[PDB]
Length: 115
Length: 148
Length: 144
Length: 97
Image 1 (cartoon, each protein chain N blue to C red):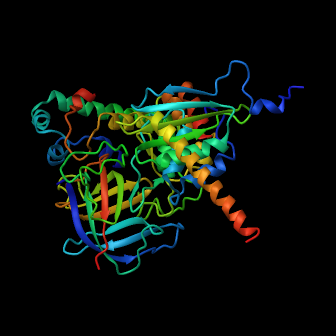
Image 2: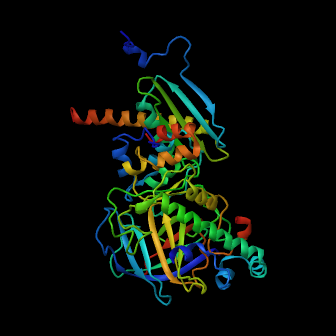
Image 3: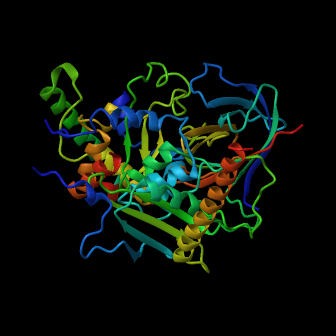
């Protein structure tokens, strides 16, 4: 009766924004990113990539409730560097790694079959 | 400076009562030229220690080699001051008790400073003259380095 | 009976003991996560206990951030023997019993039913009597 | 004997005085007589309260239920004001009384 439809976990409805940017006023150079209709599949990669950056002092994510689909990411970086730049660089590096991985897997398939 | 204490120790026991914890062992060291007993808990997985070892112990109120304090806030992107990175094992604690050998009238001749490194305790007995740098609730670093 | 009527129940309670053992050393990323789940957190990551050869925090070092205000308390673990309080090592406690909280920091000890439970004078009772309902509520939620 | 030793405030030995109370206060304590009379009257009141307690509580049970936790308040005061226990203090026992 009160069952939400299955597509509500990945479909943005009328009005919902994918990502909203808010600042953190407790500590300087901190920022919070709220992502709607996402889960650990993206949160974990983005966090682990942010931690590789030597100019990132804090990088975490959490899902506030398992029944409500929303991801919150918090990143604080050293001065003369902004968390938005850290986030964008992280996404770019992830895309580059995945593209290289796909290329190498395709060549490995080609070597394995008929070779 | 900021170095409250500095001496070379020798390990006499690792667990006189028994292996209480999997990854933590309690050294029972004795000094040399100071006659100061030590009881220190050391993470042995990260920093293995066995019997008969000699290490140089330094207890300093700051790590920055100039005098300024650290405020206790962690920051790894601060290699500029060139902290005391000549040691192998470093811990960070807070002295929580200074027992003594006082009485009603006579003053103390032997002290005993306890420091808690976030769970891993330490007691450092000895004479009351070279143990004067310790005041309770004060943050303290510990630095170890095994001598070959 | 002038005791706290609610306390930690059996699953945070079976796990806070394991968290507060001496052996628990936490990596940088694990500390990041756990602090991400703290609602009453200032925003400053404390200095690790073990600083070399690899930065490691400790379970007590994070339960200290959970504990509110400046609460002073002394409890006793449920496996504390009858000789530690008498013989030597009174304040050294080889088995890590004799919980001590000074200035809102878990200096030593293992937390169990006798510290976070629904008994008189427990840590939660002291937190209530000292800080109020509005802070004890956050205490419960953050612990869990 | 234990009660007297623990609650008497010997003002005669004067070495414990120099060790525990400050120098400007120990001279005042050793010079005044009204201070000494008040300090003796305090112990008299404590002895009478001890007898009243022993009448109220036979079978010697110390455990009791009271509204203010004085020992924990004292601990909080010590930690709040950064009191160092190894040094003589500036608290006048007459001010305490």
